[PDB]
Amino acid sequence: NTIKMVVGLGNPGKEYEQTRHNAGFWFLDELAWKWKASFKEEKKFFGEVARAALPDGDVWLLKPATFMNRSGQAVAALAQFYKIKPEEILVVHDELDIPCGRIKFKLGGGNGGHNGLKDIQAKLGTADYYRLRLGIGHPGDRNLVVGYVLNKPSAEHRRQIDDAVAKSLQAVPDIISGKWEEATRFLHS
Ligand SMILES: CC(=O)Nc1ccc(-c2csc(N)n2)cc1
C-alpha cells in the first residue's frame, strides 16, 4: 500500500492533554484502537511509536514528545530509520480555518501558521506531505490564537471533535491505498 506512517500532533504532559492543540493526539489514540496497536516509547525517535499490522504492509504510528514546534525532529527520525518518503506520510493536526466537527483533506500547501507543521516541513525538506485537518474553530482576533489553542474546548465541541475523528476513521482504507479523490469526496460531506 501507500502512506507508511501516520503522525498525530500535540504537546506533552497532562497540562496539555485536554487542549485543542492536541487534537491530532486524540485521533491517533483512537486510530491505534482501530488497528489493535499499542504505544511504546522510542527514545531514538523522540516519541511514542506503534506498529500497525496491515495485510498490504505495516503502518507506523507516531506521537512526538518533542513539543509542537520541534515535531519535525520526531518525524524525520522515523522516516530516516525506515526509509519513508514525505508523500508516504500523513500528519493529523488542528485547523482553525474550519469549525468544530468539519474535517478537511489536502496534500502539502500552506500551513496556516501552525508551529508543528512548520517544523515538520523544515525537517523533511518539503511541504509535500499529506495532512488531515481537524476543525477546532477560532476566536475573533488572531492575536488571541496562541491562548486559544492552549485551552480546553470542552462540552459541545469536544463531542463534535469525537464525531470528527469517528468519521475520519472510516476513510483510512482509501487514504492508505492512495485514493485522494475518493476519500476527499467522502470527507467533505
Ligand atoms: C508560542 C506558541 O505557542 N506558538 C504557536 C504558534 C502557532 C500556533 C498555531 C497556528 S495555527 C494553530 N492551530 N496553532 C500555535 C502556537
Image (cartoon, rainbow, N blue to C red):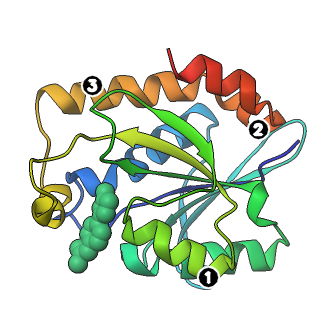
* Residue 89, label in figure: none
Q: Is residue 102 above or below residue 106?
A: above
For disc 3, the marked residue is: 160
Q: Is residue 87 above or below residue 55?
A: below
Label 1: few (<14), some or many (≥20) within 10 Å?
some
Q: Is residue 120 left or right of residue 141?
A: right
Label 3: few (<14), some or many (≥20) within 10 Å?
some
Q: Is residue 55 above or below residue 156?
A: below
Measured as percent of width and height from the top left, residue 164 is found at: 39, 27
* C-beta proximity under 8 Å, tags 1 and 3: no
Q: Is residue 59 left or right of residue 42?
A: right
- Residue at 53 percent across and 80 percent down: it is 46
Query: Which structural element holds mark 3?
Result: helix
- Is residue 140 visible in the rendered structure shown here? yes
- Residue at 20 percent across and 57 percent down: it is 149
For disc 2, the marked residue is: 176
* C-beta proximity under 8 Å, tags 2 and 1: no
Q: Counting residues from the N terminus, which is met first, the one under dot 2 or under dot 1?
A: 1
Of residues 58 and 145, the one drawn nearer to the viewer in this rendering: 145
Q: Is residue 72 left or right of residue 114?
A: right
- Residue at 74 percent across and 72 percent down: it is 79
**Quadrant of res 39:** bottom right
Queried on whether the Cβ of the residue with tag 2 lies below 8 angstroms from ligand 1, the answer reads no
| Cα separation between marks 2 and 1 | 23 Å
Q: Counting residues from the N terminus, which is met first, the one under dot 3 or under dot 2?
A: 3
Query: Which structural element holds mark 2?
Result: helix
Measured as percent of width and height from the top left, residue 80 is found at: 77, 79
Query: Which structural element holds mark 1?
Result: helix
Of residues 49 and 145, the one drawn nearer to the viewer in this rendering: 145
